[PDB]
Image (cartoon, rainbow, N blue to C red):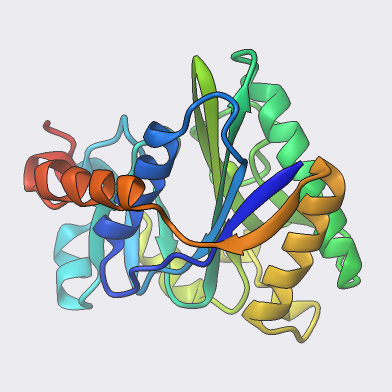
Length: 245
Ligand SMILES: [Mg+2]
C-alpha cells in the first residue's frame, strides 16, 4: 500500500526522459513499491514503438521549428508534447497480461482525479490504435480529447503512461501531426488550474482509487544507472528514434 512518488524530469531532453520511463519499468521486480512519476517534455513529437518517423511526421517541419523527435518503448500513435502537457507514468506489480483491464483501472483513477477539479471526463470508446481520438486509452471531456495513454506488460510488472493536455499549443499539436483541432482540448479550457494543481489532484485520485500511499521519493542509483545505459545505447541513437534499430 506504500508507494513512490517521483518528480523526475529531464526537460530539454525528451529522449533521456523516455529512458527514465523504461528504466523504472525494466528495473522493477514483482513485489516492489508501486511508482508514480510526473514529468514534462519541451517541444517534441513522440512516436510509438511500431512506427517510423518518416510515415507519421514531417521531419522537415519539426527541424525548422526546433521540435525534438523521439520514439517510445510503448506502442500506439504519435503525439505532440510541450511544456503545457503533464506527463505521468505508473509502474506496478502484475499478475496477468490483461491490457484492457490496466487501461480501465488507470482511467477510473484519472476520472476521479479530474472530478476533484470539477471536470467531468470519460474514457474513449473504441479499440482502434490508429484513430486520433475516442480510443479506450484516451480520456475525453465531452467530445474533446484531453489525454492520451499507452502501456506495456511483462511477467511480474506493467507500465502505463499518459500525457494530459493542460495548456498545450493545440494548434501546433495539430500542425505537426500528419477538424482534428476541433477534436482536442486543454484542461484549462474548462477549469483554470495550474500544472501542480492537476498533479496534486492526480496524486489524490490514484492514491484513493488504487489505495496506494504515494510518498515523495527519489530514483535509485540502480534505476538511474539503467536509464543512462538505455539512453547511451538506445534512446540517444538515430537508428532507434527513426524506427530502424
Ligand atoms: Mg490514447
